[PDB]
Length: 298
Length: 298
Ligand SMILES: [Cl-]
Ligand SMILES: [Cl-]
Image (cartoon, rainbow over all chains, first blue to last red; front, side, top):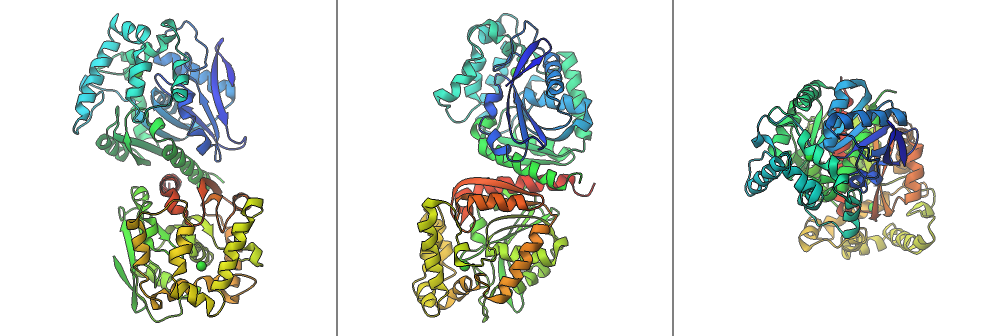
């Protein structure tokens, strides 16, 4: 499906009933609603599932904008408005979680519950990016820091992401335990056939809140995380082992620090947890919605 | 662990933080808490899990009793009382569901929620045993009816179940889609080394509420089903295809007739759904409990 949004368009996948609660599925970099393809059918029995492609991603429009975090904020807000969604569960990964947290902070009453994984938080130092404390994960964590430092460097970032397509070709498969089939990988490639098309994919790592910068995003996410910590709505945190942005020991501590946040351990997993754990995530989210709906207002 | 119950004892598996809500896992014929072994670890993070072995099953005592449905009721009540459990979620399959429905009918305030599958219901005619409307299933359903009619026949039942051990050796593996490993099958055999020890296994099919008989169980399960249909507590129904006691079409209609009952389709499955869907069931139940607990007292 397609929705007109701010003079452009956003593509979205939709499934479920009509009178069911809405669940918005929010992808990150460099994915699209494609990543939820095997999860949607497991949640559709209990909810009206809506999975937008972020502006510049998947089958959405490609306007000549900056593709900064606040650009995605604006386009997602306009999409929510266009679709007439007045409240929803949020299910999110990667930059999807930053969008979810910021949305929940501004509109606390909108959120029925938040299910999240491999999420973004303000990172005081580069050592906080891919922070982990177990064996051969440090090789992988340090490399991830080196690659992302370069992504954030003028000229270098352009060469890696726009020219060499490294986020699609390396980082993505790098964050999935199993090897995708050709037919599963192809829809990740099709939105990005050219250097210019890859502008949003380069913009996102330059938005990551690291060592206080970019300051506008860093401050907004500090604020969003304060609101999350004070929030009362149901939460579900998924973690893989060793994970990427979120290590198991951190996940445990983080979930315990919040109000009403359950921790679900998935097993072997990196960044793109949906591709290795579609069944487990789908079944968990579906049970969770069913339980909340069974005791919610009525 | 072991608890003294009515002059005998019941074995039970226990896992999870003991300040968490309790979940009681109730197995049926001819199984034990063994059947939950791959589900417990998935529910443990959100609940204090208690999985008893029914009297005469698993590692429980083998007292000199009839092992009728109401013997199980009395022993399970006495177990719950001994453990000091004042409310619980219930997760149940087979005769476990009959005990669950009956407990819920008598003590609905005890029931935090009920997750169930392949459940027993009053069956007016033998055609309601393994009831199916699907052409290709009719042969299988008729074969099932033929064996259970024999189990219920004086003399013949004893030869099949006590002498030849057919419930353990044929019925159990017959209701699992995969083939259990030798190490997974062994603990299903060890409770039943002798014809004498198999008395509870023979008692159960003779308790099934078919064509009005035995009248006590039939009437109790008639009332319990009316209670279930009116009940307001959260419920989850799991189904397999084709299932055994519950067909997919029936599950759908049944779930829809209930209040606050979500339907979870597992895919290919017969009667002992835990052995084929441990991860899906565990993940769903854990999510459901997490969701209910997040919205409870507040
Ligand atoms: Cl990024
Ligand atoms: Cl039986």
